[PDB]
């Protein structure tokens, strides 16, 4: 009736009771599981999400049933009944943002969930103001390499007027320039956004590591272009502890992983621009960004520099080079004194988070395929851990690209 | 778009729609409210409709649907059930059904080979001694001195109130695990229980790290009987590393033949409780899981110490570096010994080819993403980037409760 969840390394068992709090359907049915798919394919409804949320908030501060709790529910009813919508109090927004992170099933970093700096940017009325808020977020989160989790929340969606949006999917990414011969210079994942930036009048570089500008959009306005001050964008040159030639590859990556395309939903309210940042787990850079064939795709280059036999899969040249590239990321971040976490440390801390959440809430939604690192899966404890995936609210959700 | 799941490959950008899932007559463990895809575990009217379905599959596969022979086989099946409560497969129906069960297996990455399976028919078997002879024959044929061949042997089906044929071992070839005075295990900790059952049934145990277990074989309504595999039948590979000379000194080894013996083969509602099957290894199975799982041989630290790695800190990636080398030792050693093996790059490339064959042949392919993606270097292989749809099609292999 409630799922049994087993750890196959330790033989331990728990039952997930939290999943019964889910109000929103995922993509699976009893006929077929779609858990590996990356994306999904009135006033009465909003009123009940708002009440549930408010009840969640008062219970978190152990004031369920208090005067303040009753009056806050009344304010919400009154506001929705007159206007079709309502507004959160700053402390509620702060609580809601932390829960959305807590509830995010694809995030291996959730042991940190209670430590989140929340910037209230709901008094934003222009793309220019958005830029200032974003620059302040970056500065704060970066903190000369001693990275601090942060979210900045721009004004909620409103009925029949356009959304505040950040067109970039990350606050910091590298340009991808489609070339004469159909190869790509830079990050092939960012060709389409790079082309939007130029079409909105950016003067592009021609390097492999050109930091993109921001396209910021205030309601029903053309997006506006803003170049990030280069001193705000902390970057780490990549070199290798023992392989002296690695540095000559001229590789580098940015310190700050900052998501800017997801929608933050709290209490039925939607925040279409609400960028958030933490710190990197080294496999995102070392394995995916640098080694994916449709990304920087450097594996063969590295393996050749290591003089490995590239002619056959069975020499395991790919595996060997992937490991050295990940080590080089860790070492370089450590050398530059910029916060990073390796995939062993991160998954061990995630296991601890599972245990905390089990006692706190009776379960924890997790997407096994996202939680298990892209190299050395079974070498980490999360591989051997069964997981239950489901949608709780508050939530981060994916949304359509604004163009 | 089409009212079927849309399946995307994120490396190549290509899209397909799975229409095959519409054929699934059995529910998995997911609902709209929660995904349970990462969990390792989960009479006349019913039988007849399963039987009719399988026979339609058989006649379809030989392109004779609606044919006079098709309707006659249907009538024959219902009459058998009508008068006996059960029915029996023709020989070519069994060959087809066994290959289809393998084809349908969502967790098997080796399915490009599905059409090439030697089906040994052992539905005449009537004793544990005879099961032993059949199993020994299978092992000999399958191993083929290192040039391995996929094979399954099918013992008589489950029958109305009569005991099952069962092999108690989960695999035909496994190593003993001996519970020690100090609570540790010598050999394979996975196999403590089966090791301890073999002893209770009179096996004289060894005390190595790599002692091949005897077989505990159960004919209908008898206690299981014990059979020692003659050692010259069990091909093993000593492990060495191509450049690390000390690796051979560790005395590690593995057996050639991966042979599952505890799974139930279901075909048209008929249940084959003993139907052991075998192929050849993918190298990560041995080098990553068998040798490096913490709860298995657990050799990662020993190998990292030999490699002189910093095992005191996670960020040295000592675990990753040791695992790679062990995996390389597995591949090198099987290649040297001329024993068929496939690495995880070549296996996953071949499974991508299989997905495209099946897209055209049947409109989809049930696959379990967590099982298909290898346990090291996942995203370096093409399957990591491929969305997959998982559902139960029959014929099927299914897990069964241990007989004890
Ligand atoms: C503090 C350090 C953090 C670490 C080490 C971390 C780790 C990760 C990793 C490795 C992923 C998978 C990323 C990928 O493969 O693309 C991820 C996903 C995610 N994390 Fe975190 N995280 C951190 C902080 C945060 C914060 C502050 C938030 C929000 C406040 C957050 C929310 C999310 C969400 C919503 C996803 C999924 C994004 C998507 O579906 O594309 N995480 N996390
Ligand atoms: C020809 C070479 C083959 C290769 C390389 C191969 C590969 C694999 C691998 C790597 C696994 C996962 C095992 C694990 O993680 O423990 C597996 C599972 C499986 N394979 Fe294959 N396979 C082959 C042949 C076969 C054959 C001949 C059959 C049956 C006729 C089969 C049916 C299955 C089934 C039913 C599973 C799931 C086992 C379970 O759930 O415990 N495969 N295969
Ligand atoms: C199709 C699709 C769906 C989906 N939900 N996400 C994506 C891309 C996800 C993605 C890509 N690059 C980068 C990130 C950033 C992930 C990230 C975020 C944070 C806050 C910390 C951290 N260590 N890592 C996320 C694609
Ligand atoms: C709880 C549980 C459930 C389940 N369905 N399977 C298992 C064990 C699966 C398992 C473990 N070791 C070994 C194998 C053999 C897998 C195997 C089988 C064949 C035929 C070829 C090949 N390369 N590999 C299978 C455990
Ligand atoms: C198809 C598959 O779901 C897709 O490649 C997923 C797999 N696991 C992942 N895991 C993480 N953390 N990030 C990813 O982008 C993906 N991609
Ligand atoms: C918890 C999780 O489902 C479990 O550990 C799975 C993950 N993927 C696997 N994949 C394969 N091929 N074999 C396995 O035993 C497992 N174990
Ligand atoms: Zn599912």
Image (cartoon, coloured by chain):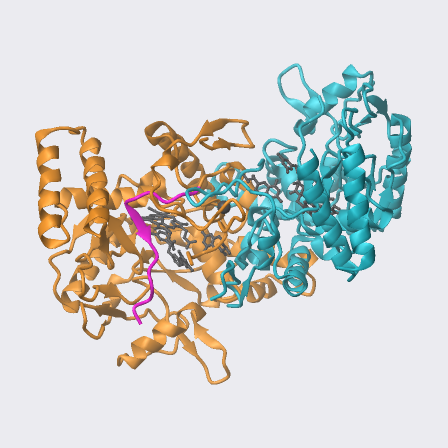
Chain colours: A orange, B cyan
Residue at screen point 78% across, 17% down: B199
Q: Relative to residue A396, is residue B28 depicted above or below?
A: above
Rendered position, B302 above or below B361: above
Residue A290, compared with residue A146, is above or below; it is below
| In the displayed structure image, the side of residue A373 where residue B360 appears, left or right | right
Q: Which of the 4 quarters of the picture holds residue B135?
A: top right
The structure residue drawn at horizontal position 15% and vertical position 68%, both measured from the top left corner, is A128
Q: Is residue B6 left or right of residue B208?
A: left
Where residue A140 sits in the image (x, y, percent)? Answer: 21, 53
Q: What is the magenta segment's predominant secondary structure?
A: loop
Look at the image and give the residue range highlighted in magenta: A389-403
Q: Nearer the viewer, residue A189 or A363?
A: A363
Q: Which picture quadrant has residue B175?
A: top right
* Quadrant occupied by the C terminus of chain A: bottom left
**x, y percentage for residue B96?**
79, 51
Q: Nearer the viewer, residue A211 or B303?
A: A211
């Amino acid at each position: 009736k409630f799922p049994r969840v087993k750890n196959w390394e330790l033989g331990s068992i728990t039952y997930d009771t939290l999943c019964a709090q889910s109000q929103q359907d995922g993509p699976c049915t009893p006929r077929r599981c779609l858990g590996s798919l990356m994306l999904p394919r009135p006033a009465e409804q909003l009123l009940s999400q708002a009440r549930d949320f408010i009840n969640q908030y008062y219970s978190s501060i152990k004031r369920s049933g208090s005067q303040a709790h009753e009056e806050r529910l009344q304010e919400v009813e009154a506001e929705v009944a007159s206007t079709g919508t309502y507004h959160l109090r700053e402390s509620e927004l702060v609580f809601g943002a932390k829960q959305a992170w807590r509830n995010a099933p694809r995030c291996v970093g959730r042991i940190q969930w209670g430590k989140l700096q929340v910037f209230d940017a709901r008094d934003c009325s222009s793309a220019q103001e958005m830029f200032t808020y974003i620059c302040n977020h970056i500065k704060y989160a970066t903190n000369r390499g001693n990275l601090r989790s942060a979210i900045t929340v721009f004004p909620q969606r409103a009925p029949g007027r356009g959304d505040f949006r950040i067109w970039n999917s990350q606050l910091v990414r590298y340009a991808g320039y489609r070339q004469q011969d159909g190869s790509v210079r830079g990050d092939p994942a960012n060709v389409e956004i790079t082309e939007l930036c130029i079409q909105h009048g950016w003067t592009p570089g021609n390097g492999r590591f050109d930091v993109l500008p921001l396209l910021l959009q205030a309601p029903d306005e053309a997006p506006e272009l803003f170049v990030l001050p280069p001193e705000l964008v902390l970057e780490v040159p990549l070199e290798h502890p023992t392989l002296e030639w690695f540095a000559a590859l001229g590789l580098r990556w940015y310190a700050l992983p900052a998501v800017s395309n997801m929608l933050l939903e709290i209490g039925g309210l939607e925040f279409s621009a609400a960028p958030f940042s933490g710190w990197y787990m080294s496999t995102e850079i070392g394995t995916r960004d640098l080694c994916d064939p449709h990304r920087y795709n450097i594996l063969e280059d590295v393996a050749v520099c290591m003089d490995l036999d590239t002619r056959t899969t069975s020499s395991l040249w790919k595996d060997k080079a992937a490991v050295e590239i990940n080590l080089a990321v860790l070492h370089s971040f450590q050398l530059a004194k910029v916060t990073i976490v390796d995939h062993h440390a991160a998954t061990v801390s995630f296991m601890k988070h599972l245990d905390n959440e089990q006692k706190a809430r009776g379960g924890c939604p997790a997407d096994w395929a996202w939680i298990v690192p892209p190299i050395s899966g079974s070498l980490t404890p999360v591989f051997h851990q069964e997981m239950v995936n489901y949608i709780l609210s508050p939530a981060f959700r994916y949304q359509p690209d604004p163009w």
